[PDB]
Amino acid sequence: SYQWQIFYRSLDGSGAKE
């Protein structure tokens, strides 16, 4: 239920960090 948990999940590597 979060931006990443919902988006990043689909994104191979959203966050720049490892």
Image (cartoon, rainbow, N blue to C red):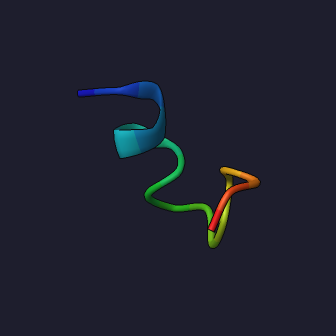
Expressed as whole percent of the image width and height from the top left, the position of residue 5 reads 35, 42
Position of the N terminus, as image quadrant, is top left
Point out the residue furthest to the right here: 16
Residue plotted at (66% across, 66% down): 13
Point out the residue furthest to the top here: 2
* 15 left or right, relative to 16: left
Residue plotted at (51% across, 43% down): 7
Position of the C terminus, as image quadrant, is bottom right
**Front residue of 16 and 8:** 16
Residue plotted at (34% across, 27% down): 2
* 11 left or right, relative to 1: right
On screen, residue 3 above or below 18: above
On screen, residue 5 above or below 2: below
Which of the 4 image quarters holds residue 9? bottom left
On screen, residue 3 above or below 16: above
Expressed as whole percent of the image width and height from the top left, the position of residue 8 reads 53, 50
**Front residue of 10 and 17:** 17
On screen, residue 15 above or below 4: below
Expressed as whole percent of the image width and height from the top left, the position of residue 10 reads 51, 61
Point out the residue furthest to the front here: 18
**Front residue of 7 and 13:** 13
Q: How many labels does the image show?
A: 0
* 8 left or right, relative to 5: right
Expressed as whole percent of the image width and height from the top left, the position of residue 17 reads 68, 57
Residue plotted at (46% across, 27% down): 3
